[PDB]
Amino acid sequence: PLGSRLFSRFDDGIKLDREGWFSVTPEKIAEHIAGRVSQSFKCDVVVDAFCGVGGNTIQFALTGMRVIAIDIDPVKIALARNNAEVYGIADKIEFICGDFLLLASFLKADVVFLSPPWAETFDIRTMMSPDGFEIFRLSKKITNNIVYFLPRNADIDQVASLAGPGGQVEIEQNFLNNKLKTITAYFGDLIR
Amino acid sequence: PLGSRLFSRFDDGIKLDREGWFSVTPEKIAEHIAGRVSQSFKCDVVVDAFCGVGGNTIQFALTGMRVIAIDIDPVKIALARNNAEVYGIADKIEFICGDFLLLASFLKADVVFLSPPWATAETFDIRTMMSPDGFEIFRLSKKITNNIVYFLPRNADIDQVASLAGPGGQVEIEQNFLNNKLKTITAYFGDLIRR
Amino acid sequence: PLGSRLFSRFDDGIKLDREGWFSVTPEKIAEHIAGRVSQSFKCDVVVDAFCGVGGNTIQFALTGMRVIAIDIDPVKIALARNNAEVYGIADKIEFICGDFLLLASFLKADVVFLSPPWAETFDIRTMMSPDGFEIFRLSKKITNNIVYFLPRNADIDQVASLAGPGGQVEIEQNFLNNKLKTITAYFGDLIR
Amino acid sequence: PLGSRLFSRFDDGREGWFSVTPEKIAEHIAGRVSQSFKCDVVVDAFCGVGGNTIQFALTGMRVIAIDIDPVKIALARNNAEVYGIADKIEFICGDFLLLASFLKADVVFLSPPWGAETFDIRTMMSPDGFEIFRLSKKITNNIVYFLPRNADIDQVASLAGPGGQVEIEQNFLNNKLKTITAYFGDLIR
Ligand SMILES: Nc1ncnc2c1ncn2[C@@H]1O[C@H](COP(=O)(O)OP(=O)(O)O)[C@@H](O)[C@H]1O
Ligand SMILES: Nc1ncnc2c1ncn2[C@@H]1O[C@H](COP(=O)(O)OP(=O)(O)O)[C@@H](O)[C@H]1O
Ligand SMILES: Nc1ncnc2c1ncn2[C@@H]1O[C@H](COP(=O)(O)OP(=O)(O)O)[C@@H](O)[C@H]1O
Ligand SMILES: Nc1ncnc2c1ncn2[C@@H]1O[C@H](COP(=O)(O)OP(=O)(O)O)[C@@H](O)[C@H]1O
């Protein structure tokens, strides 16, 4: 290891949902990440590399950013598409059904948001599919401004080693009720 | 084991999706189930008990049936709601976020559709390997109606499944194939059985 | 308007200044209604159709009945759930956030309790939102055992007509300090 | 009209919230007041069921939450527990105007009841918006006034005194003006 790592905190919490329950959902963190990214230097276009049902994609688009939302699964794309439609921000999003690793080399964007398919320590190389180092390498062809959404037990030496020697990484730790839940790693101009 | 068991077959297949891929998705089976159910005797209202993102709910609503769509997860309900909105059939559906086992005693419908949360073993035990308990799920569904659809893994215990119909009762086991390999089964009960 | 109208009385308890309750239906009246409903023939499950923060719901639940409590406002539902737990009867209630008129055709219950959103004579078709006749029609799909909580100036011809031609209605008049405040109308097997 | 008026903007995010003050702006408000110099204790003067109270409490501030209606207070107590911050709050059921002269706090948050092209805070709030502010001033200079879009900024600015400073934070929902948050004292900037 040979670079500076910033450690920060974000506190997740219960929300009052439209069903009348007090719930913990992905939305609070997604909104926080989107808010941060959209305020960073020259960050107008984001690739949501593994968009799934479009939770993060929606949050990016709601800040006025343009999104290239990618998922290998056409059922996920259709769902994400419908989801964006009702939020009234579908015109901010281009959905592409395909393999991010095969698309990455042909894209132009200011940011790549990474939430890939995810044990005492988490090995991003052997425990993600595809290879979490390969995911980042391909993201790097597009931009240095990368967000990595990672489990709490993720190897911080590995994560920091992605910044290159000796690059900076912010490790934003996500807490619920004072217990560590997940980590959001920021790279490039996303660090504050 | 006592009573009748009918074995039937449905073939799944590739579809040409709007992304320009040839793919297999849950839609074809879901559409088939909705078609069959909607043609059955006096079947106008269905409870989709574990609706998830609303795949089966959409297919039921698309045939003209009213749907009570239930999921314990409000994130799923939201997605299902938005999904239905775009299809132009949201007015056919009432979404309830809650536990099906706590809601079932208070519902009125003609049909219950069950696709509950499913070890990797040779035989699937519906009592122990489903949460909640698959016999308990069925028992609560019976308070509503005899017309019940159960979507189950290929290795489901047919003796168990047939025992849900009770001693001397009828079940239909509709086997779902993709390229001649068995993928899943759809069990029909009550007036939903063929003929 | 042909049929039978019974007129009864209930005397509300005097409340000191600055005391308040969760519902426009006073606690003592709700208690009285719940007590009456729970002793009626085969009356174990009640729908509280416009439950608010659960003032009436709590009173039904305290008698041992099971309650389907419905409100279109997710804030009310979430506050209602909290209240149910305070009174130790959350296990007796199923809260549903939704439109009563849309949910009614899918419910199973023994009793429906109606306290809908409201100068000289009160018109239930005109001065309730939604339409008071419509609310009753939908409640009728569930059961004949209906309780209608109404203003003192409610048109008794209208109220009686809901019972159908030749039908029976009970108009329980609610008195606070020997002055008329409100009415509670009973239908079906709830009539004394 | 005299003194200084700083202007700022905040962009908001079948869903409902406990307060007329949206969760996110209350969050925003509680965030910047808890950042302010020696601001540890806040009076939520018309707390209702505690929507704003919760947000102040979540920053780690202590809250004196006041409401004249005992139903609101009881509901607020439950909510505080759900959010795990009940030990940060003292609820008091009473009239803020009658309790104000007896309180000690660093911040007063005002979101009074209402009771027109231009909003007159003196005649269109119940009680009088000037009276409310005067009583809050006995406690502290650090006051937050949550107000409708059509608020008379001359009137609002006059609360700061001759040559006084006020910050008018405009709350936008989808590029459109919704409400304003006025800051006084050390809460400005
Ligand atoms: N190579 C890939 N490129 C783009 N998207 C992918 C790729 N591999 C998987 N995905 C998608 O990434 C998302 C997250 O994966 P996963 O955690 O498996 O799904 P889930 O949320 O259903 O459990 C899924 O929506 C999946 O379709
Ligand atoms: N008791 C319940 N009542 C209603 N819905 C439930 C209940 N238990 C689980 N569910 C929901 O039923 C579906 C079961 O699917 P499951 O296999 O667990 O999830 P997933 O589709 O994410 O893999 C989920 O959408 C889950 O939220
Ligand atoms: N169609 C409806 N279905 C169910 N509940 C409703 C409907 N319309 C209004 N409500 C609820 O009925 C309750 C009574 O309404 P209202 O008298 O307007 O109350 P309030 O002044 O207390 O908000 C409210 O809690 C409201 O949310
Ligand atoms: N003098 C007062 N002191 C403290 N709280 C008050 C006073 N007057 C009103 N309140 C409270 O202020 C809150 C807001 O008032 P209002 O807008 O009337 O509320 P709402 O429409 O939510 O009932 C209410 O919760 C009310 O109880």
Image (cartoon, coloured by chain):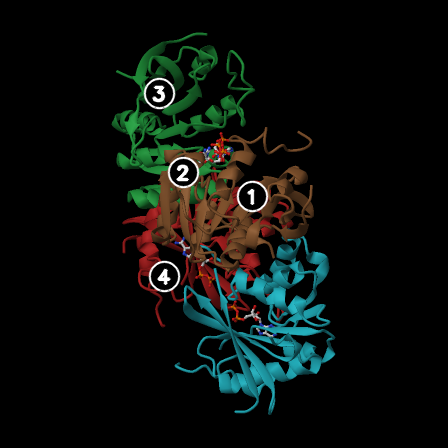
Chain colours: A brown, B green, C red, D cyan
Q: CA distance from mark 4 to mark 3?
A: 43 Å
- Disc 4 with disc 3 on a shared chain: no
Residue in the picture at 41% in, 23% down: B151
Residue linked to disc 1: A148
| Closer to the eye: label 2 or 1 | 2
Q: Chain of mark 1?
A: A
Q: Pointer 4 and pointer 3: residues touching (CB < 8 Å)?
A: no
Callout 2 and callout 4 share a chain? no
Disc 1, SS: strand
Front in this rendered view, residue B81 or A185: A185
- Which disc, if any, is residue A103? 2
Q: Is residue B139 visible?
A: yes
Q: Are marks 1 and 4 on the same chain?
A: no
Nearest-to-viewer mark from 1 and 4: 1
Q: Hey, what amino acid is under mark 4?
A: Met
The residues bearing labels 1 and 4 have C-alpha atoms spaced at a distance of 54 Å
N-terminal-most mark, 2 or 1: 2
Name the spot of residue D15 as percent of width and height, x first. 46, 55
For mark 2, give the secondary structure. helix
For marks 2 and 3, give the CA distance. Answer: 50 Å
* Residue A184 x/y as whole percent: 59, 46
User: What is the x, y in percent for residue D87?
Assistant: 73, 58
Callout 4 crowding tier (Cα within 10 Å): few <14, some 14–19, many ≥20:
some
